[PDB]
Image 1 (cartoon, rainbow, N blue to C red):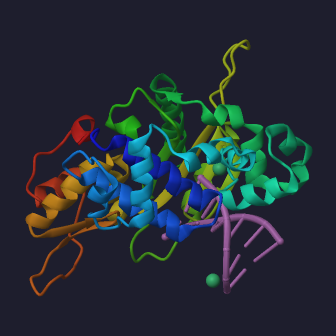
Image 2 (cartoon, rainbow, N blue to C red):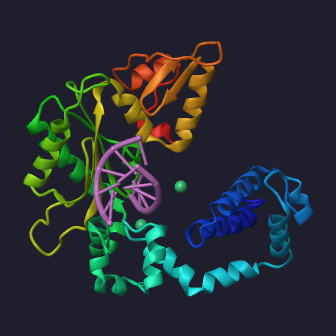
Length: 327
DNA sequence: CATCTG
DNA sequence: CAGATG
Ligand code: NA
Ligand code: NA
């Protein structure tokens, strides 16, 4: 956790680059198990050979650990940090909509910067376009104080459109969090479930409403169950308008809301443990359901849930306020 | 995993 | 349809 930190860190830089700049999924994947295991390792790696001993730990990695241990630095790490091409890739990639893939294509064409991008607005698709237009807002965190105004709106409109709609704002926003990066709304309706064959309307009506009143600004992706947008809290009495915020809305069958809700609320760590405990308790849990574990190895059949409560109960645990869902 | 692009 | 992005 801090005893093999540098190592796990350098290793992470290295892994990343393979994947992002080169295409080295294998190598990349290589640096990764490596960093994971060294990360788990209980002592202070005092040398290459020492590490090598570990699984995932091969000869070049070892070599590398050696040089790093030997001197506070690594050549290759130094070479990669300079290289403009690599840097570009890391940069372009910050644009919502631009993945590494594309980052390569553009760089090869010479688009390496933000201006470059503007100039070549033709080469960008809609998503990327938006992404470019709100690069700044996009990277700005979302203060919970805004979150509340947001939440306040979305819920009011959802309500208007149907009394029967059930919306929830998952995310850290839900676990306490003083700020967040994006707005995540879980949605369901009684009239939509596991079997129930579809009802796209269910998701479309709301999106519509949201744009009606102007909260939703642009559409990133709009499917029959998952919508990806941009929204903005009305600029009051002109002098201070807000940044544009990423926002997502997803329809869920009513018969798997809470597991979802639970699920998305996090944290990853909370999940796991909960997940693990469920397991002891003779159960299973994933994004959509909780299932009674048979003995033949495994086995299923969806337990019936009406709240986050029903869930815990099953695994016979202490109902946790979302705040304390931390770890 | 769901949506998009091409 | 394969392949990309989130
Ligand atoms: Na990006
Ligand atoms: Na292939």
